[PDB]
Image (cartoon, coloured by chain):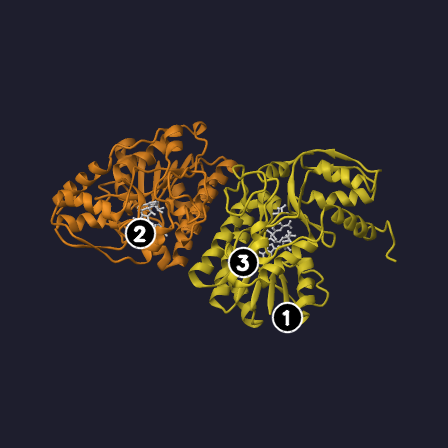
Chain colours: A orange, B yellow
Amino acid sequence: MILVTGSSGQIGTELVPYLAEKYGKKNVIASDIVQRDTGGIKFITLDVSNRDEIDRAVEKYSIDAIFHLAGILSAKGEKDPALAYKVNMNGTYNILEAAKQHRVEKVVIPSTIGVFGPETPKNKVPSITITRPRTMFGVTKIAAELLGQYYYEKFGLDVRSLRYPGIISYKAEPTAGTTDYAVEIFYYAVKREKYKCYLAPNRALPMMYMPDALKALVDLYEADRDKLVLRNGYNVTAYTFTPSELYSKIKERIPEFEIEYKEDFRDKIAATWPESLDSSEASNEWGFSIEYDLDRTIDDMIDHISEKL
Amino acid sequence: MILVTGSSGQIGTELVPYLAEKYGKKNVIASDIVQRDTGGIKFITLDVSNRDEIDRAVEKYSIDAIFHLAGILSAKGEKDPALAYKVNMNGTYNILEAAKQHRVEKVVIPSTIGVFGPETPKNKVPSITITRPRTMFGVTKIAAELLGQYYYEKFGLDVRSLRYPGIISYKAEPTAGTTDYAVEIFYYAVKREKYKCYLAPNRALPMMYMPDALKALVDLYEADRDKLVLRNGYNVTAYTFTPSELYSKIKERIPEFEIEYKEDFRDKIAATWPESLDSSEASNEWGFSIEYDLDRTIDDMIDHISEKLGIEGKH
Ligand SMILES: NC(=O)c1ccc[n+]([C@@H]2O[C@H](COP(=O)([O-])OP(=O)(O)OC[C@H]3O[C@@H](n4cnc5c(N)ncnc54)[C@H](O)[C@@H]3O)[C@@H](O)[C@H]2O)c1
Ligand SMILES: NC(=O)c1ccc[n+]([C@@H]2O[C@H](COP(=O)([O-])OP(=O)(O)OC[C@H]3O[C@@H](n4cnc5c(N)ncnc54)[C@H](O)[C@@H]3O)[C@@H](O)[C@H]2O)c1
Ligand SMILES: C[C@@H](O)[C@H](N)C(=O)O
Ligand SMILES: C[C@@H](O)[C@H](N)C(=O)O
């Protein structure tokens, strides 16, 4: 049995059915503190900050594996660092301790480029590098990777993690995140509405499309334990672009599209992150690969977003 | 008014009177979960994992600065990672948040070479480097540095830290760490007994003598704001040695002692850490310096330990 925490978020929304298709509907349980449609898949309310809740769920459902998605992200984190610490720090600690006590074969955690800071090289960054995050989210996330690796080295709990870039998707609505301009922009485009972008025109960031994001997570999950070396902190990426680049490419498709730049705190967050990642380790150790290049993602998004409008 | 957290430990035991001497006994409050003689300086019971206790102390004594020493060290930490997490991680958060909410001007935190891991370069490591610790202790400590820096950048709270190497001292006996052998060996030397060392004969580690350690922390506390660029994570060191080197140098003074090597878990810990540090940043930004080189530390420790053990009577 697989438990997914924070199932209602950007990734959860799609991962749950992905897991059900791969491993069977009876074998997944979705969980969050906020409920959404899981298409029949079993759902339970679970606050990761309550260790007890976790202990109870893991027992009652005979949980074998956990995809621990619950968290506060970079923007919200700057708005409410105490909340981020509680959910991310406390929450992740609770998950690890609970998993370690019980028979938890595997815990998979989505980490982030948010673990990087200004001292981290901006281009082709390898996984082993400077990690001096400047956001409460980032601090919590590097802590997560370190804890995870510790639990593995110390207790033999199989914790695995990769570092996602910005994820572009259509199934779940964006949530005003630092990288979410890359999703919002498509909504505006299909309506031929001028977009007001909160990141600088030339703010380059690594990104990837959700189909590849889901595949990566699952490939990491599936990898053979004795075959991972790095194990936690795998950089993964598909492409790097700036808001003006993404806009220009969209406009090639939807020429009436316009944009204006009104940068805010989220730009400042982004500025602390690298521009592009080296994802060799993930490819070598577990065969991470990308099926959707930028063009494909752009057209797929326009296709899906107009049509769901 | 200065509060010291974890004052009963190796560092606290000496920092408390060091602080009182410099700023006055009335302006220093010692605190710990375990009391020990403070030589007339005010002591209060305080468990840092209990936020309400911190709040009460800070309120009552109008605390202006906190030297936050409370914590579980590398070895003890591996025996009880859950204790280390609770004390180190949530204790530090509690301190930071309390200071912020109250009007504590400065917080100083002693970090550690424990923040480093196998991937960290072994020689003359600088402050900005790979930080992938493999002890719970080390995880908490890097978290502490990051949180401390966050508290400055986010809220404007003046949080500072340096990274200590192993510290050698004679006033208090360290118990819960990996670098302790460098204190232990002197007791055996002075008694002319065989020392059983728990680290490999070749296990190089950076180290420094307490006097220099105390000065460093206080110098960082007093440093001009305008030069504090790195702010958190300053590497500091005096010298690097292996147990076989230290033994050999002590033997130069006291020929009639010996050593055997029976490595334990602690050696595995030490193996993950770098051998030597580059402390340039500390010297550049706040004037870090060392007064006790290796020889002077060895001779001073022999002196004081001999007196402590009645090899040479107090006069
Ligand atoms: N989306 C991305 O581009 C991205 C990139 C890197 C890392 N990540 C990581 O992936 C995970 C989820 O990402 P997402 O985009 O789906 O986030 P999201 O904001 O869409 O979803 C997060 C979920 O966490 C839930 N939550 C908050 N507090 C909780 C608590 N105490 N107990 C249980 N649930 C709680 C929210 O209600 C929400 O449904 C996080 O760990 C995040 O840091 C995401
Ligand atoms: N001694 C060193 O070589 C060295 C090196 C690097 C960093 N440091 C740091 O210096 C600080 C103290 O070092 P030390 O060598 O004196 O340690 P120590 O083990 O000698 O003393 C630690 C003190 O922490 C106290 N303590 C434990 N839990 C507590 C709690 N919940 N509330 C209040 N007090 C609590 C203990 O009772 C003890 O008196 C730590 O933060 C440590 O990580 C020390
Ligand atoms: C990708 C990750 O950093 C997240 N989407 C954020 O905006 O914080
Ligand atoms: C190195 C420092 O953290 C402490 N002396 C230890 O042994 O843990």
Q: What amino acid type is highlighted by mark number 1?
A: Asn
For the point 50% across and 47% down, the residue is: B128
Is circle 1 on the same chain as circle 2? Answer: no
Quadrant of the drawing holding the C terminus of chain B: bottom right
| Residues at marks 1 and 2, CA–CA distance in whole angstroms | 46 Å
Task: Please tell me which residue lies in front, A140 or A103.
Answer: A140
Position above or below: A242 against A229: below
Disc nearer the start of the sequence (1/3) = 1
Q: Secondary structure at mark 3?
A: strand
Circle 2 marks a residue in which chain?
A: A
What chain letter is assigned to the residue under label 1? Answer: B
Judge: label 2 CB < 8 Å from ligand 3: yes
Which residue in the structure is indicated by mark 3?
Answer: B160
Q: Position of residue B223 (x, y in %)?
A: 57, 62
Which residue corresponds to mark 1?
B27
Residue that numbered label 2 is attached to: A178
Task: State the separation of the CA atoms marked 2 and 3.
Answer: 29 Å
